[PDB]
Image (spheres, coloured by chain):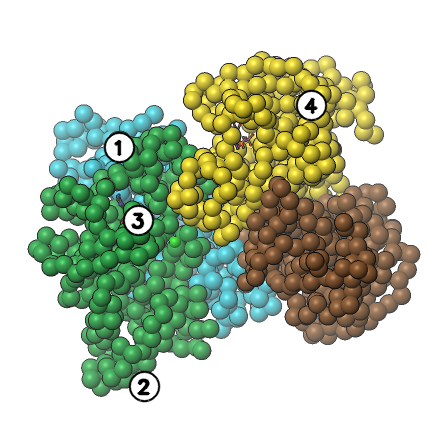
Chain colours: A cyan, B brown, C yellow, D green
Amino acid sequence: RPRILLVIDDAHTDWSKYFHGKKVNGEIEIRVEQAEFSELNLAAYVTGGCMVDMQRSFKPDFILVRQHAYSMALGEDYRSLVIGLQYGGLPAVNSLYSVYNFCSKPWVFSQLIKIFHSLGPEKFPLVEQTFFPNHKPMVTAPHFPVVVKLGHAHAGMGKIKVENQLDFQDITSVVAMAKTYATTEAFIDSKYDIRIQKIGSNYKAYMRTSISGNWKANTGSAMLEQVAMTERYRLWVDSCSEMFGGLDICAVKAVHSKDGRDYIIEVMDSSMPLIGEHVEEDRQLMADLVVSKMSQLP
Amino acid sequence: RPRILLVIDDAHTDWSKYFHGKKVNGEIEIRVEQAEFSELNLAAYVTGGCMVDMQRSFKPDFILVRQHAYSMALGEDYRSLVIGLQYGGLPAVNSLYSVYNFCSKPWVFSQLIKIFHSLGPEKFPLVEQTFFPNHKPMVTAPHFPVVVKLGHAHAGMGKIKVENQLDFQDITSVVAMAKTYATTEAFIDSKYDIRIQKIGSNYKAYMRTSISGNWKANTGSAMLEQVAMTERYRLWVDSCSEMFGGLDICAVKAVHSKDGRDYIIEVMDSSMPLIGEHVEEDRQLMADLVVSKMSQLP
Amino acid sequence: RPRILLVIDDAHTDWSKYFHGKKVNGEIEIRVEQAEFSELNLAAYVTGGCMVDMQRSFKPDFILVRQHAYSMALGEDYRSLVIGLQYGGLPAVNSLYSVYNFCSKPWVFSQLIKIFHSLGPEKFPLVEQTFFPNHKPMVTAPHFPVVVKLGHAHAGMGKIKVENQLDFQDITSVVAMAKTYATTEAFIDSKYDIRIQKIGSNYKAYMRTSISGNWKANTGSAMLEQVAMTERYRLWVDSCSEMFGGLDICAVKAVHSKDGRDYIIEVMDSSMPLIGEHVEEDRQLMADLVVSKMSQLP
Amino acid sequence: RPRILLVIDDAHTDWSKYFHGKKVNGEIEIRVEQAEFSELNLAAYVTGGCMVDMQRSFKPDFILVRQHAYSMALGEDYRSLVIGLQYGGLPAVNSLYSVYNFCSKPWVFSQLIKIFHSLGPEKFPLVEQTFFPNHKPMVTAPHFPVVVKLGHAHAGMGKIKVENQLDFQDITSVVAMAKTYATTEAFIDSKYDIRIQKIGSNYKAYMRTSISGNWKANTGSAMLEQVAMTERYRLWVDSCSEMFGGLDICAVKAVHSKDGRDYIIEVMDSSMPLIGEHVEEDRQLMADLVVSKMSQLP
Ligand SMILES: Nc1ncnc2c1ncn2[C@@H]1O[C@H](COP(=O)(O)OP(=O)(O)NP(=O)(O)O)[C@@H](O)[C@H]1O
Ligand SMILES: Nc1ncnc2c1ncn2[C@@H]1O[C@H](COP(=O)(O)OP(=O)(O)NP(=O)(O)O)[C@@H](O)[C@H]1O
Ligand SMILES: Nc1ncnc2c1ncn2[C@@H]1O[C@H](COP(=O)(O)OP(=O)(O)NP(=O)(O)O)[C@@H](O)[C@H]1O
Ligand SMILES: Nc1ncnc2c1ncn2[C@@H]1O[C@H](COP(=O)(O)OP(=O)(O)NP(=O)(O)O)[C@@H](O)[C@H]1O
Ligand SMILES: [Cl-]
Ligand SMILES: [Cl-]
Ligand SMILES: [Cl-]
Ligand SMILES: [Cl-]
């Protein structure tokens, strides 16, 4: 019988095309199921595995997670589906263990702080961010302008450049109303984003400039240019890939000031956006990695 | 047996002092219990009435509601207590029917819009506000600076003066995190707030200026001066007092531009803040009002 | 220009077919837009009206509300869209005012209690229900078995027959976890549901028996039989139609014990399910009513 | 300067008494602060550490977590405080990494399933539970009576013994209102609970029987008897103690059927209840453990 791969993704792409001809241990056919989280439900059993309902029912053998499991500004919460697939004992890329731990940005950021403490600010320039568990301790910032980031949200949501204290005070009331946590960090007058990605043993670096006048350079029209990988960029991404027992797919993003300094602001996992000119190549590297992992199982 | 009045209030006042010596129809004594919403629970019955627990247990005959039942920035939600008291058939000031309908600012604002459509902008100069059910349709505003007011909140919370379109975009992105509705309206360069109140048949008008540099004139230190009532002001509040079957206590607030134009921005009910130099007279007027209502009961 | 009717509905039906040939004041063409709540967004303006986006944009002139605006067990909350359409000043069936007040079952039930108090248990046999604002006051019930109903939910959701005190205690912990209110009432050993509906001046009565062995007789396969209207049934539905300024469409449901007694358990508004053999006739009566209301406008 | 230990606990005990006279490396004094989660707030910084406010303000050096950080039936959620302390780089017992991962019972259960897959049912007799991400896939169970356990809750809350399929259907309908996940497993006709605990290198086994007629043997009055540790029990707890990078304090609980079979039902961490006649010795062992950990710091 074919091994069933479930690709969980919201991207407008047909994942089966990247698996054409690929067989587990060069022997067993791979059936590719594809759905976004909102289309999936399951029961999971101590005795072993998951029965998945896609709206059709099936027991998956392997998961590829391409979609964010938690997106607070969209009102989407699939963390319990992640719990279920892990309860079923499913092997996955990235590991369901890491995917679950990635469902809170400040929790992930706490791992970046460990890297920072170990490597130092010259090797790993992490942005000097502050974390507030709720609105109450938020009074001011040491440096304006400041970037305030609410909760666990993506694609620029929940994020504001605050210019002054009066404005900061009014934003803290929004943190209160949202009943969530928040972080603050210096706004960097940045020329472009830098993102270093790792897919298995493939590395790429890109610079990204907003061509729509956006300080959130990952929103709206952007110009993307692939740049040379350096050993400095490689240490960033390799260091990040070590967390939560290991990340098969990940990326680290920095902002690059007009003064020449980089500041690491974020890390991403197997649900990272695919950017630049090699998106089709990147999905094929992901499919290659998945088949290799499937073949390493009994 | 004394008739039991339950005053629900968060203010630091002994309400019993305004009722001492007051009897229902000059005959029956009034027992005043007082608590804030957070200290109260109840069961309500089709067969009639409520049993209230106060942390003492008792069956109230009449309710005075002085505290806001819903405050999103405080994370306080006592709407189900208001449902309960109405379910029990309790008479109150204001009516529990009106109190419940007051737990959504834009719901109440829709009633102001009905008055505005009827009386026109000369007699009832309602601010030209826009309502958004969520963040999605918020793109821009016709005129900057703009005041954005998020959800249902009090005492200046979730109210933000936005200077320009770029800043507006970031505000829209954090509004999303509150998962609630929002309103926009033009910022008025205002000399002072005007508030017209009604307590039964007693009318007062106050002007209020921040003496602590706040565009939110109802926050921080202010100077308050009582001003003469006019026919113009009397129509504003009288009109407002007809909503939701009739409001015994209410107030209408306007801002007054440097160029001499008034803009109505808010209506308030029996939980309105008491302001200026006649706070104790106002509480006494409220007690006299409750007693006249209590005297209509069997 | 055509008058735009927005029918908000989740039913698999094409509403335009019921409006074919119908013209406002026999003169103006009616453009029928149809969507479910999840497909709609809007901005609403003090200056007048709403701009609606359906996923196409338009200003509606009249609303028909066929869909529940709030369904807690489905995680669907459209109350802010109701607020918006009312803020826009939209005329509707039923009134947006009543539709909003219908978005809480115990709040509606409090109106049934007023009818009960006025008419008496012989003319209006309301079930003797208790309301709890939260889990805390819930200890036991006076009669087992009891029906416990959590929050504001439809189609049988949030509802359980509890046989004993130990079971009741464990259900109260579910009320706590759901952070909602609940009601309790005697379980009636019922032969069938009785539902009396009023669409304008059209009345129908049905009896409904579960043929799938369900105490929730409105879930699963049922046998429906139309029965004769009586003056007793007419008083029930006419009395209910008076609430929240008037209900153009409504229904009242009772359960009928094996001992011969009826117990009114619920009232429904313009989003009531359509049942029995005359669903197509009922939608046409609704369309007739809508056009008549549209014609009574300027 | 004394090293500051923050004990987070809701228990009515003076933790300072177990540390009096204990010095970090026999040299530096320990200052013990104690509070429950509800009394604490903080800011955490990339540059290092947390400032904690206790309602006093201070920077802790080490944390002991004795209180549950997440209790859905109590409406208590302190997960963002746990994030904060980890963000600050705080060492703790148990590790803040493990504490956070323990805030979802089924997430933790998935780790028990890994141990079960490895050791088998003879050595590690895990109850054959099913996990449901939400109410939708809950239709029936293979064996009645069944224990349904809703969400993430403690002290018997949301745990319901369901006797049959008809009752199960109603439970499913109220589970939906909690908007969370749920688990089902066979009810064991149990003589007593067995709990095996580990505190550092100290092991105890207790049997516990309800003396107040409760299938939930950890609720109400019980009799507790310490029993001999065995290799069998030692493997259960040792296995469990390896999860999430290592647990310094943990316990495994089983139920023991009338026919003599054990079924493992739960694992607990540093917030485990202290039980039986050695509660004070157990707290002292915990203090000795914290001191040995604190002695490893600079
Ligand atoms: N401190 C900062 N200074 C300057 N620019 C910043 C800063 N933080 C974020 N940005 C910019 O804003 C963009 C979005 O912020 P980011 O923190 O990456 O959130 P996000 O869009 O939610 N990320 P994601 O989860 O991948 O969708 C970044 O790509 C930068 O271009
Ligand atoms: N459009 C506006 N232009 C200028 N000032 C405004 C405007 N809207 C509000 N204000 C000012 O800000 C204050 C607070 O706004 P308001 O809408 O009254 O919120 P609030 O404080 O939540 N009211 P409340 O519920 O009584 O506590 C008002 O008293 C005015 O002084
Ligand atoms: N007290 C009761 N005794 C016996 N049967 C009852 C009782 N209450 C409800 N039922 C039955 O359960 C069904 C569903 O309960 P109901 O209170 O009508 O909730 P609902 O299904 O959410 N209604 P709706 O909002 O129209 O979808 C009723 O139609 C009756 O058949
Ligand atoms: N499947 C089962 N069969 C028989 N008894 C059970 C079963 N599951 C739980 N119990 C009993 O019910 C008690 C409570 O269940 P448990 O799963 O421990 O929930 P809890 O009280 O929330 N645990 P905790 O987090 O330590 O407070 C257990 O101590 C057992 O005595
Ligand atoms: Cl998001
Ligand atoms: Cl508030
Ligand atoms: Cl529902
Ligand atoms: Cl709990």
Camera-side mark, 3 or 2: 3
Which is in the foreground here, disc 1 or disc 2? 1
Q: Nearer the viewer, mark 4 or mark 3?
A: 3
**Residue sitting at 84 percent across and 63 percent down?**
B204
The chain containing the residue under callout 2 comes to D
Quadrant holding the C terminus of chain D? bottom left
User: In whole angstroms, how far apart are the C-alphas of marks 1 and 2?
Assistant: 61 Å
Of labels 2 and 4, the one closer to you: 4
The answer to whether the residues at label 4 and label 3 have Cβ atoms under 8 Å apart is: no
Circle 3/circle 2 CB separation < 8 Å: no
Disc number placed over residue D143 in the picture, else none: 1
Task: Return the chain for callout 1.
Answer: D
Q: Amino acid at mark 3?
A: Gly
In the rendered image, which quarter is residue A60 located in? top left
| Residue at the farthest front position | B1
Which residue lies under the disc numbered 4? C232
- The percent coordinates of residue B21 (x first, y second) are 78, 68
Of the two numbered discs 3 and 2 on the same chain, state the one appearing first in sequence.
Answer: 2
Cα separation, mark 4 vs mark 3, equals 50 Å
